[PDB]
Length: 577
DNA sequence: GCGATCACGTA
DNA sequence: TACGTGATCGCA
Image 1 (cartoon, helix red, strand yellow):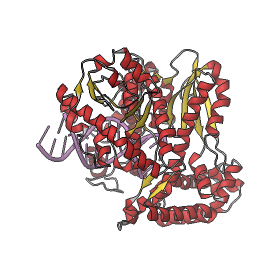
Image 2 (cartoon, protein in one colour; image 1 turned 180 degrees about the vertical axis):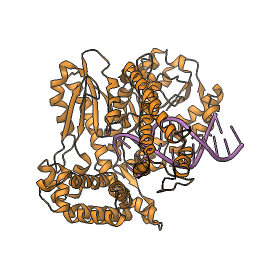
Image 3 (tube, chains in turn cyan, green, yellow; image 1 turned 90 degrees about the vertical axis):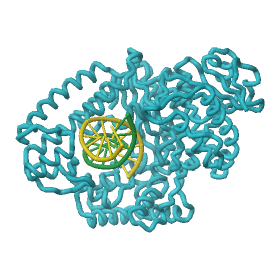
């Protein structure tokens, strides 16, 4: 039983309530709110949004920090409301974030999935109510109102058992003091968006299309015929049947044509270099130029990413529409894409600050490896020092290739890759990659001990934890399949590193947001990308930020080694280098 | 019109 | 390693 309400009564404006502000469109930016449900001690209420959101008492209640609301995915609601000029405050419990902290592997997508964790099944999955894909539609008011009230009732019923388990896990503060405050910061970041210079992007796309026409023509005269270069089946027939290049790698369906294979085939035929070049130009044009231009809002000329705070098993943020975490950087041709990200006001600048080697610093701290801690206490180039140790040479004797291999070993630790993966990145044998690793563990015995100990702890406890008590369950750690078990072992080692680094960055964003307000700066966070925070600010604030931001980031936690922050500012993201 | 599948970019 | 995303193609 629920009141399908016609107007807002005071009964719906209690001190504590479960609240559903339903946004069905996957991209919630400027998206409709289809319905509102409130469950509190006085009953269960469904409100049409046009009513509720025009009611001054309702809107005042939404924005009253002392009126506590329990929700699922409150950022979606907060942002949808921001686009309507309405502030959502007082969200004291977000079930999406609670479920995520309790077990990130569950993939909790909707209220129903979180409710199942506590054997609560009186709510349907969103996909059963709205449908999937083409046939996705908002159902009739009776069906919609039942669904929203059921979601709000589930939230109401589930808050206590979820907070109880969080407390047993010592994750209650992680929820309340880190993830929920971050959610509000991310909602403001997403709402602010980042201004895009679409003229520059369109000019770049114009350039790429011309080179792509040129390289594509050269490819066709080399293949003796025309074909769809973007089809790895057609390309496979041109390279490996017509031109009879060696087959160095097979895929499930046929001939591998990854850039790894093509680089190896380059000496045999001039086509191969042009294919690689076509692949890189086409990646830029399709994915980044055309892809970015599709999601720039023509009103604001901004992109408004959506940060997914509750997806990764490490606690890292992901982002979509656009995904700004893979804007190119390595190749100069691609890094120029970042010239298109500009401050949103005249006489403002982009300020970007990034942790230097935060993952290895976290590893030095957690493993208490004396050699690694000393390397960071001396602020050495970690890759050079790793080369010196592994190859037992002095700094002047480290060749670029020795540093490259040491860097690949460090990369393998940071991202938890296998010996096979290291071998593949170093283009060496698996046996050779293995002996590289062993030489590393002789130089860093503390890291070796941490690796062994964390795997034993994962086996004993069932999970591993980060510095701020995020956990990752690893049921595959006892699997009898070697590849499955090795992956779980590498995740046991890696997640305390990657996840603690994510924890620090999140804490830094919270501290930064409060410091910006304390200092009454106009600067504002725009993006969190890997280990980098990107802000925009009046040019007149750059000198204050140069001092403030690195300090806040460096003081976010106290490790046994310093945190180091590099920072730059400029007129574009590219120039903030 | 989905859904693998392959390839590629940051990690 | 991961996630996100593209184009292709294979199944309807």
